[PDB]
Amino acid sequence: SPGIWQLDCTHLEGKVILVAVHVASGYIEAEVIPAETGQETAYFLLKLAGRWPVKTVHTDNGSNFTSTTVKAACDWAGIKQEDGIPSMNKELKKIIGQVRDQAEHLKTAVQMAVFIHNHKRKGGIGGYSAGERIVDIIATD
Amino acid sequence: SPGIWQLDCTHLEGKVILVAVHVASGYIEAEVIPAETGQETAYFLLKLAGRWPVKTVHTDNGSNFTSTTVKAACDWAGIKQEGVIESMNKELKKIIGQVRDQAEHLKTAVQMAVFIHNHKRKGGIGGYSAGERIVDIIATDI
Ligand SMILES: Oc1ccc2c(c1)OCO2
Ligand SMILES: Oc1ccc2c(c1)OCO2
Ligand SMILES: Oc1ccc2c(c1)OCO2
Image (tube, rainbow over all chains, first blue to last red; front, side):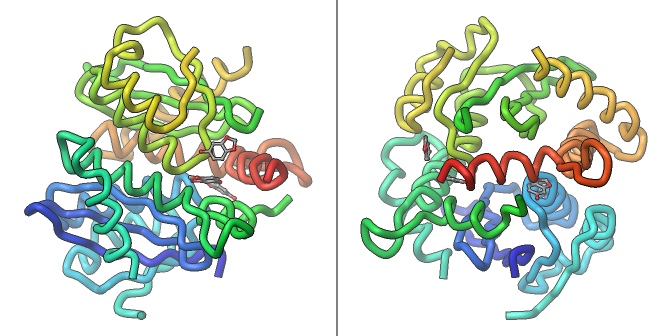
């Protein structure tokens, strides 16, 4: 459970946003990429796995994930790739709209949205953020 | 403090690597960029602060860090701008060379080195990696 990430793509203004969600916490990592190629996807995963302990990724089984370049990346990083195994994308586009008018470029609006999402307290003032939840869940002490 | 980072640049292959080290842990975030511009620096900072609770960043004297875009990003993100972390930097550049050949582009080699550094257990049985240390520091703070 703590090592499981869900990857999805979202398309906005003709650009591609790759989103990784840590399933247990709702914490997100996201980047605008040129296009869903095997090299860009592998690069994204390698970055993700270098920053958090990624054991398993669930993907939508897009052609970018069937590429050997992605399989090679997952192998090197020790990630179990789970293709086709079953709503951030709505939440995030919402937040992206709240900040869109503060950023010249979409890529910046995306990172602002990531920031807001991960810092937001869920479940009343007594609750916690996705950021707080992921470190609590992943901490080994 | 859990909120303190040190940022620095390294110039390699006519490229710039931006490196941020979480001071208390040795954990690193790094990106390869075409050039050390105000725009790229501000973007790097926004990404960092959205992923980890960044309170203060220590930087070099660069004109990039005082640009208006960086100031706007730091204001929005709540970031304040201002001898072993120099080591994590020489460590990283060493790992880069030890893997640089395994990869086509510099940036792949850089992210491989970040992976190796952050996952690497320090000390014997009983040791921790930098990645485990940052998570433990922040979880304890919360
Ligand atoms: O461990 C974290 C604590 C707070 C955060 C976070 C991670 O992402 C943004 O906010
Ligand atoms: O983005 C942040 C989230 C939590 C924090 C912080 C910054 O400073 C201390 O606590
Ligand atoms: O337990 C870990 C926490 C963060 C990490 C990691 C392991 O490897 C890279 O980043």
